[PDB]
Image (tube, rainbow, N blue to C red; front, top):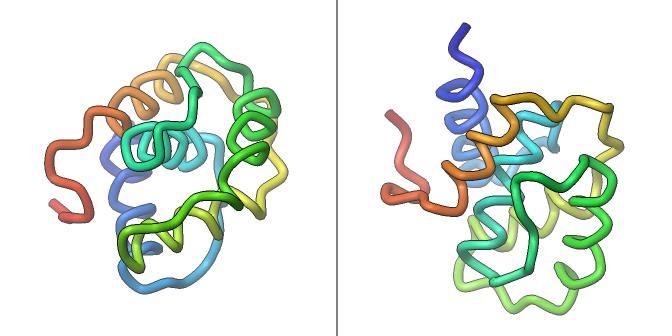
Length: 107
């Protein structure tokens, strides 16, 4: 039921507006993917939610963002308490983030 387009658009709008925080694991996995792409942090779709966040948090604060949207990714990843959701859609969202071909462009 449209979880993938919703999560992508939500994260793009948050980074463009520089408002709000992560509110779901669907958003977390997409955001994690973008961090892999933009910052090269060694995360993968198969990591569990807290594991994924721990790996990102070991390095996100040392990253030098290229623009305001990447700077907002650091804000998103430093302020979230994940639930146990790690389904087929969280995995696809991670892959969508890491391979993002239209970064910061809403549909």
